Image (cartoon, rainbow, N blue to C red):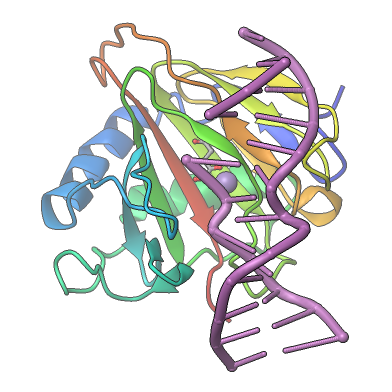
Length: 202
DNA sequence: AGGTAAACGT
DNA sequence: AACGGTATTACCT
Ligand SMILES: O=C(O)CCC(=O)C(=O)O
Ligand SMILES: [Mn+2]
């Protein structure tokens, strides 16, 4: 019944914290605005993104990279809000990863139709640390597979406040998001946000 | 050697 | 529309 070895879903874990989380997303984006990044191959992603914390995930021509500087503003990413950090630590603890210290939070925003094709999170040098993923606003279908792209997928609806954590044996599993269905949510109005916490540095 | 980008047709 | 090809290569370090 558990998501996978080392992996768990904490349904509605972030429900009570969500209004403050969303105020702080708005604050982060007021400094480093959401933008749709362009892949190395030249395609614009459907998800709009920004980052907070000491390191931010970015693409550039040469690949994927963590950087301490937002290439759009040329200034450091905004500091990680304490609300984000406190929620992360509680969720990580509840999921069995009490020692997790993220230094990076990638904020994804899904408009209707936006998706994330199956991928692995492998840009982090220390793969001992888990990923903590917090869903806010409109629901989305999350794909969670195995070590190989063709391993069979579990498909789970992720609703507002749901937190998923993966690590250990499932750290490098393929995962993704199916094209967002249009809808209404009273706190985000017409979108989904996802916060993805990582330990990106050493 | 090995790391690793990947987001159209059936 | 769920599944899988593509990187079965071309380039870095
Ligand atoms: O949006 C999600 O639920 C997953 C996001 C994700 O996998 C990523 O940003 O790497
Ligand atoms: Mn991911």
